[PDB]
Image: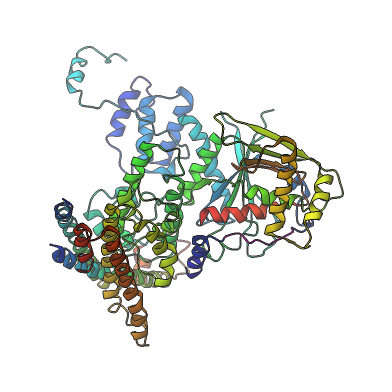
């Protein structure tokens, strides 16, 4: 309770992000990490949500919870045959901090009327979320971040079930346009010696009755030679390194078209690592830098709760 | 056993509805009526008989039912329509367990059973029932207060005013939701930990209007803390709006702070009485509470003698300065 | 009427604190009776019956 | 106009906290008789009673 008090005063003050950050390391896949499971998690469309930590969650009561979920989502389709069945699959070895709880997978796999087609995929996780672990008790299980794949009507009928069983509530996640520039600078701080995609930016003009979009493409070998002329202190990504990197990209646009894009709003960053959007849409296209992006999403998911 | 005749089947099941007890719900009678559901389909006399069986014993049936609005039977006072169709119509073919929360109908049902009360499926129904507000007054358990913190902090954040698309109908429901909070904080006599955490993030974001009276009563029932923690988060952002808004706001701050001086001095008057535990003398703790409240009144007294110079001696502010020193 | 309302509020705080300490004593007595009910149910020959 | 409305608020507040004192005394008189029945029923049924009744 006293560490719950000390986490409020960092949120009540204006400071919540450090100006000098660490370049993320090369996360090597261990032998305990399943190679055939992480290939299914790649190349998928995801919708992010934040969640309060659960109550009376056990690792041995998943067989009862699989039968209650299969008896309810058939019944919610009848109030408005179904050969569907949920699978509570547990994953191992993703954690870097030993005090984190175990992440797991929630699918909906259709049965064989002739592997079935997966219609919905839910994923509860907590990657480097150590700041919320001492603010909860030992009875609580802290899994703040949630990623969903599928329709929003299937999300709401299963998200009704977590409200009435585990005493929690789902909230929509949103990433600010200031915070897209830091994760674009982190994606240009990566190390690569392989096949790469193109760095794609998109801005929207707010001072219009209609929509106005600009597609903007940067070659990543041209982005790497632009980065190290700005990046002069190795090991740390500072406040002045990112704001001068965005200013020289704006001054490159300024001498051709005479349009200030610093008044606009950045909404989509798509690089060789991953693609991002402000309402919670992500497309992870890399497996070597998987947990470095997902720890940054739990760095924002605790901040919307607190 | 008269359900083997198919022609008497709505006539048997209305007699089965009115004569069912807890011991009459049997698991083989679950098993036959699920077989009659599979053979001759959905009938409203068989779905209403299983609706009472889910009303009596839900653990014996593994098949869930819809909860839709149906009359289920002959009802709604149609006894003259029954007698007109009676001539020639349709006559040719010590307990350490838990007590359920839905069986609390009135006041003396909770007075007989307070030592066995279960936990509900959501924390939003605590504000709906006043009988559940009596349970919060005498229980000092830790995870029943943290789950109430995790719900209502998400309620005030997503469903606020400036996060929406400026709907007047949702702002009326937000005004009706804040009327539930100000009656729950006065019935408990302590403010919630969600409510003072929301005012840490909304006082830089508030301008001085748009349900001013529900926001200045939300600051009135905040519990006691140290003086150095309140003044960067509340008293700096209050004084940016106090000297610059209208004089009806200037009177409503001192009506809010005189109710803040009620509930802070009410807790400190009885904190001496309920603590025999510490063998150390309490003159350092009361002396540490002495300068927390003497710098409170000398700050609002600095707010009172500066705002007198702003309006240049109006008596309408001067009635509510002397009502603050009545406290 | 304000000093009458504040006297009613102080009596409500005293009866609320007395009922809170009384329900704390009743729940510790309930855990004591739970320990005594777990202690007074030991038998070996009862399971065949 | 703002003090007579403060009087009309406090006469409404004269009803509610008198009702809240009447509810808290009704909690207090019911928790007294449940403390007296729990103190009189500390001793439960005997261990030899359960073997001979079953």
| Residue B279 placement (x, y as % from top left) | 36, 87
Per the picture, the main secondary structure of the magenta-coloured stretch is: loop
Is B230 above or below relative to A292? below
Q: Nearer the viewer, residue B93 or B322?
A: B322
Estimate the x, y position of residue D36 in percent, counting from the top left: 23, 70
Q: Residue furthest top?
A: B88
Is residue A17 part of the magenta span, yes or no? yes
Q: Residue at x 79, y 60 (%)?
A: A232
Q: Is residue A117 above or below residue B141?
A: above
Q: Can you tell which quarter of the image residue D13 is in?
A: bottom left
Q: Position of residue B83 (x, y in %)?
A: 18, 18
User: What segment carries the magenta color?
Assistant: A16-23
- B99 up-or-down from D45: above or below: above
* Depth order, front residue of B30/A167: A167
Please tell me which residue is depicted at 42% across the width and 56% down the height of the picture: B203
Left or right, A233 with respect to A262, comes to right
Location of residue C7 (image quadrant) = bottom left
At horizontal 43% and vertical 25% (from top left) the residue drawn is B42
Residue at 72% over, 44% down: A251
Q: Residue furthest bottom?
A: B280
- In this view, the residue in front, A60 or B220, is B220
Q: Nearer the viewer, residue B262 or B24?
A: B262
- Outermost residue toward the right? A193
Does B79 appear in magenta? no
Quarter of the image where the C terminus of chain D is located: bottom left
Here the colouring is rainbow
Q: Is residue D38 visible?
A: no
Horizontal relation, residue B108 to residue A34: left or right? left
Residue C31 visible in the displayed image: yes
């Amino acid at each position: 309770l006293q560490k719950r008090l000390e986490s409020v005063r960092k949120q009540s003050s204006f400071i919540l992000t450090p100006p000098r950050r660490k370049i993320p390391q090369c996360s090597q896949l261990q032998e305990d990490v399943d190679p055939q499971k992480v290939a299914f998690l790649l190349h998928k469309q995801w919708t992010l949500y934040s969640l309060t930590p659960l109550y009376k969650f056990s690792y041995s009561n998943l067989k009862e919870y699989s039968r209650l979920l299969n008896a309810f989502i058939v019944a919610e389709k009848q109030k408005g045959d179904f050969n569907i069945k949920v699978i509570f699959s547990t994953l191992l070895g993703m954690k870097g901090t030993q005090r984190d709880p175990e992440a797991f997978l929630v699918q909906i796999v259709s049965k064989s009327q002739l592997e079935g087609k997966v219609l919905w995929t839910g994923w509860f996780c907590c990657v480097f979320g150590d700041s919320l672990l001492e603010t909860v008790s030992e009875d609580f299980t802290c899994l703040p971040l949630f990623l969903a794949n599928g329709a929003e009507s299937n999300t709401a009928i299963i998200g009704t079930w977590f409200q009435k069983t585990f005493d929690c509530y789902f909230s929509p996640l949103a990433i600010n346009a200031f915070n897209l520039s830091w994760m674009a600078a982190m994606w240009t701080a990566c190390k690569m010696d392989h096949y790469v995609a193109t760095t794609e930016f998109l801005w929207s003009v707010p001072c219009s009755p209609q929509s106005l979009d600009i597609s903007f493409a940067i070659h990543p070998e041209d982005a790497k030679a632009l980065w190290d002329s700005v990046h002069k202190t190795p090991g740390e990504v500072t406040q002045e390194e990112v704001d001068l990197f965005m200013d020289c990209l704006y001054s490159h646009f300024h001498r051709h078209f005479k349009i200030h894009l610093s008044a606009t709003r950045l909404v989509r960053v798509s690089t060789s690592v991953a693609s991002a959007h402000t309402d919670g849409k992500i497309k992870i296209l890399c497996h070597k830098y998987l947990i470095g992006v997902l720890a940054y999403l739990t760095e924002l998911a605790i901040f919307q709760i607190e | 056993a008269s359900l083997q005749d198919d022609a008497l089947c709505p006539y048997v099941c209305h007699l089965l509805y009115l004569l069912t007890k807890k011991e009459n719900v049997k698991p083989f009678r679950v098993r036959k009526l699920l077989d009659l559901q599979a053979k001759m389909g959905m009938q409203p006399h068989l779905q209403a008989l299983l609706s009472l069986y889910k009303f009596f014993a839900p653990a014996l049936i593994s098949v869930s039912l819809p909860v839709r609005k149906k009359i289920y039977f002959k009802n709604s006072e149609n006894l003259w329509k029954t007698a007109l169709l009676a001539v020639k119509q349709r006559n040719r073919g010590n307990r350490s367990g838990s007590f359920p929360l839905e069986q609390l109908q009135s006041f003396p049902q909770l007075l007989q059973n307070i030592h066995c009360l279960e936990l509900p499926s959501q924390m939003g129904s605590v504000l709906n029932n006043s009988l559940l507000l009596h349970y919060i007054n005498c229980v000092r358990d830790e995870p029943v207060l943290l789950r109430f913190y995790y719900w209502l902090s998400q309620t005030l954040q997503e469903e606020c005013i400036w996060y929406k698309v400026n709907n007047y109908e949702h702002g009326k429901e937000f005004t009706n939701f804040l009327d539930t909070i100000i009656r729950a904080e006065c019935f408990l006599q302590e403010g919630f930990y969600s409510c003072e955490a929301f005012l840490y993030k909304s006082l830089p974001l508030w301008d001085g209007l748009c349900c001013r009276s529900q926001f200045l009563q939300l600051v009135s029932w905040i519990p006691f803390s140290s003086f150095s923690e309140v003044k960067p988060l509340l008293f700096d952002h209050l004084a940016q709006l106090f000297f610059t808004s209208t004089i009806y706001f200037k009177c409503s701050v001192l009506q809010s702070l005189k109710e803040l001086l009620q509930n802070w001095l009410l807790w400190l008057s009885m904190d001496i009485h309920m603590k025999p535990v510490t063998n150390s003398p309490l003159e350092t703790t009361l002396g540490g509470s002495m300068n927390s409240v003497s710098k409170l009144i000398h700050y609002v007294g600095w707010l009172s003698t500066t705002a007198m110079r702003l309006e240049s001696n109006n008596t309408f502010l001067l009635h509510f300065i002397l009502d603050f020193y009545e406290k | 009427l304000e000093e009458k309302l504040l006297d009613i509020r102080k009596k409500r705080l005293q009866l609320k604190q007395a009922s809170e300490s009384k329900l704390l004593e009743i729940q510790t007595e309930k855990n004591k009776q739970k320990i005594d009910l777990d202690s007074m149910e030991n038998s070996e020959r009862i399971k065949i019956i | 106009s703002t003090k007579e409305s403060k009087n009309e608020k406090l006469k409404e507040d004269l009803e509610r906290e008198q009702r809240w004192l009447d509810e808290q005394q009704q909690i207090m008189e019911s928790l007294n008789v449940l403390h007296s029945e729990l103190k009189n029923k500390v001793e439960t049924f005997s261990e030899s009673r359960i073997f001979n009744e079953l």
